[PDB]
Image 1: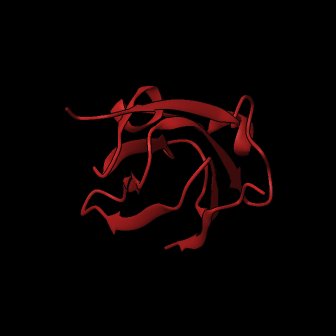
Image 2: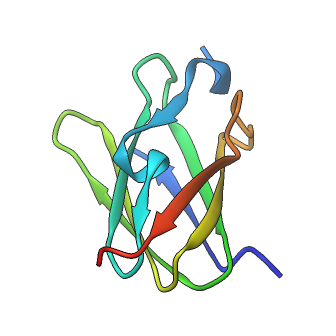
Length: 106
């Protein structure tokens, strides 16, 4: 039940200063890597933990960025609502449990 795919990646003012957004957190396509970005400007780095909870398996891929920005892309194997629970340095951030409506690309 839930926690279909999760990832804890260390990042090399607090979690309340960290908010997540991007296409990947507003909509997702079944069988497509939905990429979202986490606002880690005023944070101080630490550890980015992400758990994708949904009806089916999700493919979480983590890619780094030269500026030191965060970019996470996850697929979904089947359409539905997906609640991505994030944690920055063990903190669930303000409003992490983002439910992303995954729909069929077709």
